[PDB]
């Protein structure tokens, strides 16, 4: 098909962190030819083999259906509901939809970062500077997608709204199970 791949940074702006050191972030990755879908995120997840806080994790999700280059609304809704329940405290999603040829490179980068979970050289979690949002920004930067400028203090809820100023918006509500894509 030659259809561009999809990278969908997702932020859960109403996610509650509760204890110190707003929102959580993850990323959906979709093969534009096949609809094969991956989800990765970085956060304060348990790891018995590392004493350094912060780990990448992969969450299994359904694949989407691509029809004439587009993701069908229903198949994306199924993934968004999965991600909200499994990673997002059953809250709403604010996202952007990015396009390019990068599926294998993104998959390799994410698996490579996950391979660092037990490394003595793993960069420690930092709520301000090395967190769920900066993981995704660093991925998009690495793909050549030129994400929005990263401030010294990265707040997922604030950053995603900045990112949306220059990209396609994705809004999803878990309670109503409704998706809206907009400029
Ligand atoms: Ca918004
Ligand atoms: Ca926008």
Image: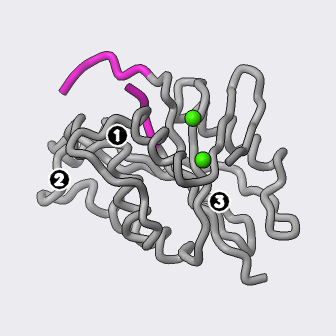
The residue that label 2 is drawn on is 123
Separation (CA) of disc 3 from disc 2: 27 Å
Badge 3 vs badge 2, beta-carbon distance below 8 Å: no
* 39 relative position to 56: left or right: right
Q: Residue furthest left?
A: 120
Is residue 20 magenta-colored? yes
- The dot on residue 176 is none
Give percent across and percent down for residue 14. Answer: 49, 22
Q: What range is drawn magenta here?
A: 16-25
Q: Quadrant of the N terminus?
A: bottom right
At label 3, counting other C-alpha atoms closer than 10 Å, the crowd grade (few under 14, some 14-19, many 20 or more) is: many
The image shows a total of numbered marks equal to: 3
Give the answer, above or below, for where 156 lies relative to 142.
above
Q: CA distance from mark 1 to mark 3?
A: 20 Å
- Quadrant hosting residue 101: bottom right
Q: Quadrant of residue 48?
A: top left
Q: Which residue is mark 1?
A: 43
In the image, taking residue 116 as reference, residue 75 lies left or right, namely right
Label 2: element kind: loop
- Secondary structure type for disc 1: strand
Q: Which residue occupies the foreground of this view, 144 or 75?
A: 144
On residue 37, the disc is 3
Measured from the top left, where is residue 77 in percent x and y? Answer: 76, 41
Q: Is residue 100 within the magenta segment?
A: no
Residue sitting at x 74%, y 71%:
34
Q: Position of residue 108 (x, y in %)?
A: 44, 73
């Amino acid at each position: 098909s030659g259809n561009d791949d999809f990278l969908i940074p997702v932020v859960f702006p109403d996610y509650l962190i509760s204890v110190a050191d707003l929102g959580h972030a993850g990323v959906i990755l979709i093969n534009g030819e096949t609809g094969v879908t991956r989800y990765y995120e970085y956060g304060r997840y348990k790891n018995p083999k590392s004493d350094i806080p912060g780990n990448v994790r992969k969450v299994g999700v359904s694949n989407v259906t691509i029809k004439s280059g587009l993701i069908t609304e229903s198949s994306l809704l199924k993934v968004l509901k999965e991600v909200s329940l499994r990673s997002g405290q059953e809250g709403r999603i604010s996202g952007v939809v990015l396009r390019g040829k990068f599926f294998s490179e993104a998959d390799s980068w994410l698996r490579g970062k996950m391979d660092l979970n037990n490394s003595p050289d793993k960069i420690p979690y930092d709520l301000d500077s090395h967190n769920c949002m900066t993981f995704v920004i660093d991925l998009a930067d690495a793909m050549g997608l030129d994400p929005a400028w990263k401030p010294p203090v990265v707040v997922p809820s604030a950053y995603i709204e900045q990112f949306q100023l220059s990209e396609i918006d994705l809004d999803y509500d878990y309670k109503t199970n409704k998706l809206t894509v907009s400029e």
